[PDB]
Image: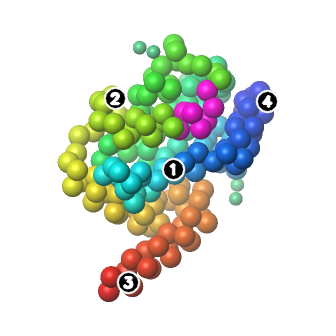
Amino acid sequence: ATKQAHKRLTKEYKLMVENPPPYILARPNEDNILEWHYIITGPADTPYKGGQYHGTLTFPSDYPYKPPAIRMITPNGRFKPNTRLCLSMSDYHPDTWNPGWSVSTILNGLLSFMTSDEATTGSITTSDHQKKTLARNSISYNTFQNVRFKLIFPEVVQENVETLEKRKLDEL
Ligand SMILES: [Cl-]
Ligand SMILES: [Cl-]
Ligand SMILES: [Cl-]
Ligand code: NA
Ligand code: NA
């Protein structure tokens, strides 16, 4: 990464440790500071309640002067997986990019957009039932079918194992 980008993104992670944004866990790949991974916890008064949504922010080589590419990995019913999402703070809008936006601000914009129904490149149309099904299955998806989640968030995989144990044992 450039030295400027590396310093900036290191500080952004520190700021998130100090004041963790509601609903959002995020950190750099330990092998590439430009590639960040996040986990959004679905807010309760949405069809995403109980869901666990992993995705990435990929900062470009010219960060902080160009925006990240924003993708969601976990199937979710709102955004097509593994696809760059057209958000106000994203690489679709380099024209109105503000270098000063924090990573928390960018991620909060993703979450705020996600819980609206506004259409944009990368969004998809599903029913409420489909979103709820995907939310319910998201923890399993991340625990068993998501290679990158296991590599980046192994401590969360272990938490997930307990969560799924309790769901299975307490309901059967
Ligand atoms: Cl390029
Ligand atoms: Cl535009
Ligand atoms: Cl714009
Ligand atoms: Na590690
Ligand atoms: Na490594």
Magenta-highlighted residues: 101-107
Callout 1, which amino acid? Answer: Tyr
- Mark 2 → mark 1, Cα distance in angstroms: 24 Å
Q: Quadrant of residue 32?
A: top right
Q: Nearer the viewer, residue 143 or 100?
A: 100
Chain-order first, disc 2 or disc 1? 1
Relative vertical location of residue 90 with respect to residue 154 in this rendering, above or below: above
Chain-order first, disc 4 or disc 1? 4
Look at the numbered disc 4 and give the secondary structure of its residue.
helix
- The label shown at residue 170 is 3
2 and 4 marks in contact (CB < 8 Å): no
Q: Residues within 10 Å of mark 3 (few under 14, many from 20)?
A: few
Look at the numbered disc 1 and give the secondary structure of its residue.
loop
List the residue tagged with mark 2: 121
List the residue tagged with mark 1: 23
Q: Position of residue 44 (x, y in %)?
A: 39, 54
Q: Residues within 10 Å of mark 4 (few under 14, many from 20)?
A: few
Q: Residues within 10 Å of mark 2 (few under 14, many from 20)?
A: few
Relative vertical location of residue 105 with respect to residue 74 in this rendering, above or below: above
Callout 2, which amino acid? Answer: Thr
Chain-order first, disc 3 or disc 1? 1
Chain-order first, disc 2 or disc 4? 4
Callout 3, which amino acid? Answer: Asp
Q: Is residue 95 visible?
A: yes
Q: Looking at the image, which residue is at 54% across and 70% down? A: 159
Q: Looking at the image, which residue is at 70% across and 48% down? A: 17
